[PDB]
Amino acid sequence: NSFLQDVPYWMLQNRSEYITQGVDSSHIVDGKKTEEIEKIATKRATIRVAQNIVHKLKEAYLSKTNRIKQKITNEMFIQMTQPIYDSLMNVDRLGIYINPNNEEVFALVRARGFDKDALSEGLHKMSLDNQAVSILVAKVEEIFKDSV
Amino acid sequence: NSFLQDVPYWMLQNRSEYITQGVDSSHIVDGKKTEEIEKIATKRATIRVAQNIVHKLKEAYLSKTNRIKQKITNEMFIQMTQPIYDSLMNVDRLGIYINPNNEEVFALVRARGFDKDALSEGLHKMSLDNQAVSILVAKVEEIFKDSV
Image (cartoon, rainbow over all chains, first blue to last red; front, side, top):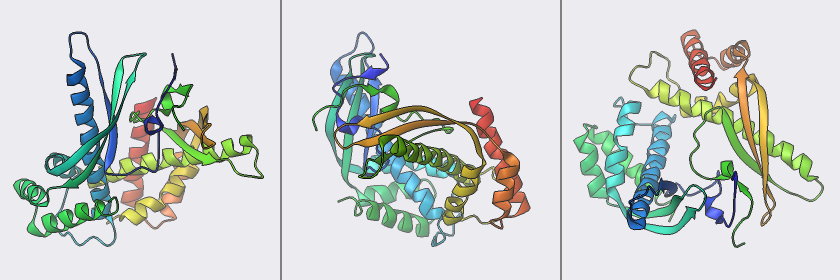
């Protein structure tokens, strides 16, 4: 009921986890292949990675050491979830756990790298200054360093 | 190692996303009874609630509809974690979970409300503008109201 069984460690809430990996789930409705459901969960998990990066970036921008002069709004940061998501490369599905109770399936993924050029192009598309694109890309690039 | 049995549904990594709710942990150590460790975990869980509130204020401050004129750095936001924390009242401890593998004591907690005048005194002590203090206190209320 309110207590599950045979639950992998990664499924537990961990305050100290890699920003480059995330977990999310999907519900198995009736007429639906298990393949599709895992596809979804895996995708949502990958979006969760993108979101973690964006958050780290807000903090960087808010930081006292920030050099980016352009005004970046919270809405704009939400917008870059997409180009960031689009630049993710080598995202490995490290695990899957199906909640037998409510038939909810969870996915655990981890992005190993990201396409720099792909990311810059996406940022230039949302009207971010060249200075900002440059610094933002440098930051993400650092993220994958403090992970690799 | 292996799987974990009897895990509460709240311990699941699925981003429950409830600002007034916090989960955190502490590891068992020689010289301390588990009940003492539970208290450490409970207090960290409350600090986490305060940290959730802080992250919300950053998003509101970063928002295009922000009216706060004063430049607030990430470091300053991190700093208000203390006053926010000190202003919390009626924090109910909803649960305790312990991973048997590593003896990590997890606690789930929930802040019912907060003492605004307590918050305002703390924020003023940080040398924030009167406009900033006023707007920040207002947004916290909006948070607790949205939970009630």
